[PDB]
């Protein structure tokens, strides 16, 4: 299992120790408070009122937690995933990333604390 | 395992099928959007800017998800719990509840979708 | 989880730290060598050639590992149980017992090493 | 998870659907009766009285269940493995095999029924 922090201003994302392999079932729980610029902060589902202006993940709100598995496209994580299996052909290291517009991470603040484990399968 | 919705306006809380027994390890993931009255909605961590005016759980924000186990006091759940063990002497059915002030649930809206499972132990 | 030895000559059985609760899923693996009297020894499935002359469990061979859950009747364990759920209304402490005829345990020898854990549910 | 039979006369072994990956925790439970030639049958720990005359696994008795993971050497399974982690650098498909001397499998009989699952990690 892995536990760590994902900083909102880390555009490259936070690599974890988790390698997702075919057939794996995983659980993720994410908590905490972060911002994509404003003084306000949002949880790992992000800001439901803010328009998408070029987010790295168009399937989650700005300020949400997302991930990549190997070199997949971004996949929403939000508050977490319960006993989840990846789409076919998706495998490799899990990288966690705050959802913002590329080039605009410098004014971000806060972080999410995230646990990831593999479940029985 | 249990999956279901917890309505923000349900003051009695949502009983689940999960009975927490001594030694159990559990995982909860909660998602969604709810309000304790305002037109805005918040995720399962609630509204970090709103003062506590007599919440059923003083250890979580207004609008957060909390629980009771048997007839315990309220315990914060927020976005979820990862491979969690209860305090000594806490056991019984898990009831999930939206954190608001007693008597003020009528103007609440939305709900959280919640998964709960028992982990290996 | 519990790990321990079950002595072949222990007529009362070996109490474990595992309380089986409704809905629990458990796994048991048992290993080792024991005898109900002869110089030979047998593994946890017992002696497939020996007649049942009044065994505590008529659904397993003499010399097999069996169990009780609370005050249930005996249930075969043999080499183990994989992600197993008990019958309806069966619950309580797990006691492991070598299968022999009551009153005839004094000439028994050896033991089984046994792991028991609860699985995800 | 995988469930299947491992025939005692199958010299090449039984390939399973389980690919053991770095960091995986697995559980195996094996049951049943088989023989390496004699009319008698033994359980998955094999025959503790028979000399090793060139077995594929010198760390288990003749007639025991063993495995390979990818192209590893043989590893004893016996009655099973509880929440087990492989040695460093061992990975790949799990193949289950009856322990006998190469070239002598033709007079073998019976089989073991085996479950393998991945555990939480
Ligand atoms: Ca920004
Ligand atoms: Ca309200
Ligand atoms: Ca005896
Ligand atoms: Ca043979």
Image: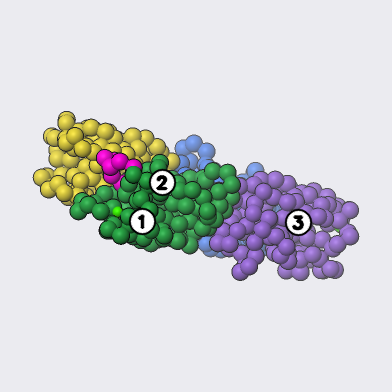
Chain colours: A blue, B purple, C green, D yellow
Q: Is residue D68 magenta?
A: no
Q: Is residue C47 magenta?
A: yes
- Image quadrant of ligand 3 equals bottom left
Tell me the SS state at disc 1.
Answer: loop
Question: What's the magenta region?
Answer: C46-52
Quadrant for residue D35, please give it: top left
Where is residue C73? Give x, y as percent: 49, 48
Mark sitting on residue C103 = 1
Which residue bears the numbered disc 2? C57
Which residue bears the numbered disc 3? B97
- Cβ of disc 1 within 8 Å of ligand 3? no
Which comes sooner in the sequence, label 2 or label 1?
A: 2
The residue nearer to you, when weighing C99 against D30, is C99
Please rate how many residues cluster around mark 2, counting C-alpha atoms within 10 Å: few if below 14, some from 14 to 19, many from 20: many
Total numbered labels placed on residues in the image: 3
Residue at point 51% right, 45% down?
C85
Question: Among all residues in the image, which is located at the extreme left?
Answer: D53
| Measured Cα–Cα span from mark 3 to mark 2 | 47 Å
Q: Are marks 3 and 2 in contact (CB under 8 Å)?
A: no
Q: Are marks 1 and 3 in contact (CB under 8 Å)?
A: no
Please rate how many residues cluster around mark 1, counting C-alpha atoms within 10 Å: few if below 14, some from 14 to 19, many from 20: few
The residue nearer to you, when weighing B106 against B36, is B106
Which secondary structure dominates the residues rendered in magenta?
Answer: loop
Q: Can residue A41 be seen?
A: no
| Measured Cα–Cα span from mark 1 to mark 3 | 56 Å
Where is residue D27? Give x, y as percent: 39, 49
Residue at point 58% right, 56% down?
B26
């Amino acid at each position: 299992a892995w536990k760590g922090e994902v900083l909102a201003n880390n555009e490259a994302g936070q690599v974890t120790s988790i390698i997702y392999n075919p057939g794996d079932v995983i659980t993720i729980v994410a908590a905490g408070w972060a911002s994509y610029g404003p003084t306000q902060k949002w949880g790992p589902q992000g800001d439901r009122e803010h328009p998408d202006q070029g987010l790295i993940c168009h399937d989650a709100f700005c300020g949400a937690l997302v991930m990549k598995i190997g070199n997949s496209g971004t996949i929403p994580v939000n508050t977490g995933l319960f006993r989840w299996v990846a789409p076919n052909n998706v495998q490799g290291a899990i990288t966690l990333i705050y959802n913002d517009v590329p080039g605009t991470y410098g004014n971000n603040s806060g972080s999410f604390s995230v646990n990831i484990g593999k479940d029985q399968s």
